[PDB]
Image (spheres, coloured by chain):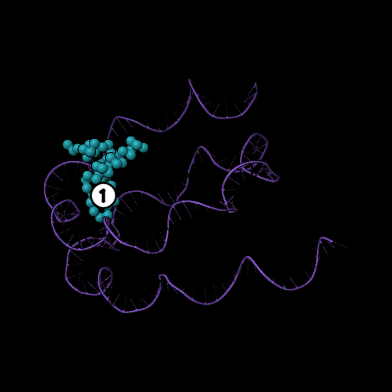
DNA sequence: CAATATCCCGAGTACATGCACAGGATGTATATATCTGACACGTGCCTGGAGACTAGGGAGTAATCCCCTTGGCGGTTAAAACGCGGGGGACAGCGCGTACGTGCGTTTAAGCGGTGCTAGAGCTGTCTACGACCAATTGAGCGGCCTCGGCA
């Protein structure tokens, strides 16, 4: 049974659709997995203010 | 006080939305990977501190009238409201582009070795530009000479 990384952060937003998005805006180099979990929850958190 | 207007409440009104569904593409999951760069280690520099002194500036004041500020000004239209015109609004279809799929083959990235371009070197080695001073010019205001208009 697969989990989802959204549940391990505790977030409603898609932590793995981000990551794949960031990996397309990246010079020629990679992106840490712990970036998607404070990339998200600093896009959610504008929702629930907007 | 009268009148035009905004506010408010209930009937009646399409479809919008939230949902359930099939299913597909991608997020996950595991194993592997090197290498980014974390971390650790000194190197050596400037950021900072700390003093003595002049001279530039800053702060202060004084005098004052410029400029702002105000009132009162006189003059003409945006607004008000109406009449009044045409124009923005709601349906029928064509086919052309856009998309999308196919197979189109151009070029880049990579790893190769060779080598010359550039960017840190100098006291380079000066000498443009940087003060320093002099000289010219114009303009403005103040005396001074000289015709004429209003008054004895």
State whether residue A17 appears in this view.
no
| Quadrant holding the N terminus of chain A | top left
Q: Residue at x 30, y 39 (%)?
A: A44
Rendered image quadrant of residue B47: bottom left
Task: Tell me where residue B66 sits by quadrant.
Answer: bottom right
Image vertical order of residue B23 relative to residue B50, above or below: above
Q: Is residue A48 visible?
A: yes
Would residue B144 appear left or right of B128 to someone viewing this image? right
Q: Nearer the viewer, residue B78 or B142?
A: B142
- Quick check: B73 above or below B114? above
Q: Position of residue B49 (x, y in %)?
A: 26, 55
Front residue of B101 and B49: B49
The residue sitting at 28% across, 40% down in the picture is A41
In this structure image, what is the colour of chain B? purple
The image quarter containing residue B113 is: bottom left
Badge 1 is on which residue? A23
- The residue sitting at 18% across, 38% down in the picture is A2
Location of residue B91 in the rendering, given as x and y in whole percent from the top left corner: 50, 38
Shade representing chain A: cyan
Residue B98 appears at what percent x and percent y? 39, 50
User: Dot 1: within a 10 Å radius of its alpha carbon, few (fewer than 14), some, or many (20 or more) residues?
Assistant: some
Q: Secondary structure at mark 1?
A: helix
The residue under the point 21% across, 45% down is: A33
- The answer to whether residue B129 is left or right of residue B152 is left
């Amino acid at each position: 049974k697969a989990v989802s990384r959204s549940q391990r952060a505790g977030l409603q937003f898609p932590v793995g659709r981000i990551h794949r998005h960031l990996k397309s805006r990246t010079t020629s180099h990679g992106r840490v997995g712990a970036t998607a979990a404070v990339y998200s929850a600093a896009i959610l958190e504008y929702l629930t203010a907007e």
